[PDB]
Length: 296
Length: 296
Ligand SMILES: *[C@@H]1O[C@H](CO[C@@H]2O[C@@H](C)[C@@H](O)[C@@H](O)[C@@H]2O)[C@@H](O[C@@H]2O[C@H](CO)[C@@H](O[C@@H]3O[C@H](CO[C@H]4O[C@H](CO)[C@@H](O)[C@H](O)[C@@H]4O)[C@@H](O)[C@H](O[C@H]4O[C@H](CO)[C@@H](O)[C@H](O)[C@@H]4O)[C@@H]3O)[C@H](O)[C@H]2NC(C)=O)[C@H](O)[C@H]1NC(C)=O
Ligand SMILES: *[C@@H]1O[C@H](CO[C@@H]2O[C@@H](C)[C@@H](O)[C@@H](O)[C@@H]2O)[C@@H](O[C@@H]2O[C@H](CO)[C@@H](O[C@@H]3O[C@H](CO[C@H]4O[C@H](CO)[C@@H](O)[C@H](O)[C@@H]4O)[C@@H](O)[C@H](O[C@H]4O[C@H](CO)[C@@H](O)[C@H](O)[C@@H]4O)[C@@H]3O)[C@H](O)[C@H]2NC(C)=O)[C@H](O)[C@H]1NC(C)=O
Ligand SMILES: *[C@@H]1O[C@H](CO[C@@H]2O[C@@H](C)[C@@H](O)[C@@H](O)[C@@H]2O)[C@@H](O[C@@H]2O[C@H](CO)[C@@H](O[C@@H]3O[C@H](CO)[C@@H](O)[C@H](O)[C@@H]3O)[C@H](O)[C@H]2NC(C)=O)[C@H](O)[C@H]1NC(C)=O
Ligand SMILES: *[C@@H]1O[C@H](CO[C@@H]2O[C@@H](C)[C@@H](O)[C@@H](O)[C@@H]2O)[C@@H](O[C@@H]2O[C@H](CO)[C@@H](O[C@@H]3O[C@H](CO)[C@@H](O)[C@H](O)[C@@H]3O)[C@H](O)[C@H]2NC(C)=O)[C@H](O)[C@H]1NC(C)=O
Ligand SMILES: *[C@@H]1O[C@H](CO)[C@@H](O)[C@H](O)[C@H]1NC(C)=O
Ligand SMILES: *[C@@H]1O[C@H](CO)[C@@H](O)[C@H](O)[C@H]1NC(C)=O
Image (tube, rainbow over all chains, first blue to last red; front, top):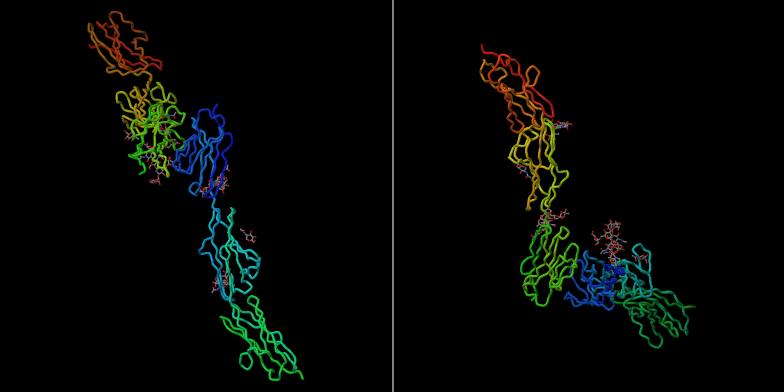
């Protein structure tokens, strides 16, 4: 009888630089001969245990009589396509299989965004592009799973698309953003973009009117938000307040927030008047008004 | 340097059963290797001096370092197509050429006409079909270069087309017809058709009135055309004339024509009267009237 393939030639799918192993099997080969050969380029590759193509990445093995195994190391995209296992017969017998090569995902340095910095109330567009086969899918997230403002006013945890535009950025939008590019092949990779925001400081004051008697210890207080962090000092009569045992100012800073106090000890009659808490940063300055008055 | 073809791979064209010789040449082959292989069927054939395909009609020769000559004996139509000469290189180098197989011409036994026979005044259609590649061209002629009646009433020496129709055949159309089928490849062949015609006889008479005196020798004469040839006898008084020394009838036949005489020696007075020349064949009979009368 004539030889015939023992098991169909199977589809393979390999990543770049890896090794590809294509396996052809034949029952009862007698004195006939097997040949591998790329189809598209119509190029002979191997015959029996002898390799033809000078392409040194290709190799044949005859470990068992059944299997004639073709091996392609350091695989490349050019190598992918159709491959034929052929048996010298009249007529000739051949089964054919496909090798799909695949590339992991990669994020580019351009136009991929870097650590960007924009003023509050402004615009931005965190771009991210990546290469891959299959053409990868890009997804944005935030390190603390924070929200991501959407163009409709709603907000979610993961936005798709290479280009993400935020309108009128807010100090809450500030944080660590992650571009994630997955092609479905390991290892998926991601780049960390830093969105920092600066804003002219602003001052809130709980009690703009506080009273005190003599010999009592009282503390004024304001609340500011400034980035970069703001220099916060007290004023009275259009003059700086330097702590002189009787009056001591403090500041308690947390991120862009700042809570400043001016603790007045043993209130004197000359202390009463109009105070001001001022805040100043690279983008402007601001102040508030607190009035200290008498009890009786 | 790398090898390269010395002379382009040339187009061949061969007839069936013959031998085909395809010649590939390469300059500076070093340790590389040549391979022949059919393109369409993607089938490897030969490599170096070793033949792969079990097709025993194929053979490689390395007579000179230049030429790697592939030889295909007892060529068949299935063999024709594209053939590639390949050199194992990375990338691979290959030049390709076409083998066109050709078949001489042949006339079939059917529906090819045979020796046909039709009555005069009737129709006929001398058919002739032939096979060949290129599809051959059929031409009709006549052995004596005679004319060939055309459907418009005109006449020529050679008509094209497989089917030739003659309307109301005439005895002049009778003769040897030749079907000729040429494909442009030797040896062109031709079949000889025989067109025979039968016709009820007809009689012409030059002198329907002849006079004679006594003791004179006179000869009557008619002219007939009959096919198949007609039996021509003389009549007088509704009775057959059998030669009895005084009267002797003759016949001079040429093809379908016949010229009959009745030579009367020493005319008697009882001889004068009404004679008749009769002609009879398979398709009917006919006669004429000659009156013999006196001089004084
Ligand atoms: C082994 O894999 C073979 C290759 O497939 C690749 O590898 C696998 C592992 C996956 O990664 C896969 O995603 C890859 O594509 C595989 O061959 C594939 O088989 C399918 C189905 O048989 C083919 O789909 C058909 O493709 C044809 C032609 O498309 C080509 O030509 C056009 C130009 O004309 C190009 O633009 C394309 O990009 C392609 O190159 C289509 O005509 C056809 O659609 C028609 O037929 C269907 C019904 O069958 C109708 O419903 C439609 O309306 C059309 O009328 C299909 O789309 C696919 O093309 C083919 N891949 C390649 C590269 O040719 C093979 O099947 C696998 N074998 C085994 C044993 O697993
Ligand atoms: C060696 O011979 C090759 C084969 O030629 C045969 O063998 C020779 C010895 C002769 O006997 C000859 O009569 C045989 O045909 C020869 O290849 C031939 O090259 C010519 C010209 O290069 C080709 O003509 C072109 O064919 C294409 C495709 O036609 C095929 O496909 C259609 C279906 O799509 C089929 O129906 C046909 O039957 C064919 O199978 C046409 O598209 C093309 O026309 C177009 O291009 C021209 C301009 O080039 C335009 O003007 C037109 O309008 C069209 O846009 C031509 O008609 C011929 O097909 C091809 N033969 C074969 C079998 O493919 C080769 O060139 C020779 N080489 C040398 C070195 O001598
Ligand atoms: C800062 O960003 C805002 C809004 O941000 C973006 O706005 C859209 C263009 C989309 O990209 C959104 O996905 C995204 O959130 C910009 O305001 C927007 O400006 C465009 C351009 O003028 C407006 O488009 C207009 O649409 C009308 C139809 O209603 C057309 O007739 C116009 O011709 C024009 O195309 C868009 O409506 C507007 N959106 C909002 C919410 O204001 C803003 O321009 C941008 N800053 C700068 C300097 O460009
Ligand atoms: C014997 O042969 C004659 C003529 O021979 C052939 O006539 C043509 C049909 C062509 O094949 C010629 O190449 C060839 O010499 C036959 O007489 C022909 O008969 C046909 C069929 O009736 C006539 O065709 C007609 O044409 C008119 C248009 O004028 C149409 O309206 C009709 O419907 C019909 O198709 C043809 O004119 C006629 N030709 C002559 C010269 O008489 C004859 O029929 C044939 N014998 C038999 C028994 O068929
Ligand atoms: C886009 O993101 C949304 C939110 O997770 C999800 O529903 C959708 O499937 C995503 N689209 C793609 C193509 O992944
Ligand atoms: C048909 O015959 C005529 C008469 O000889 C000739 O002119 C013509 O070239 C012929 N046609 C072909 C295709 O040979």
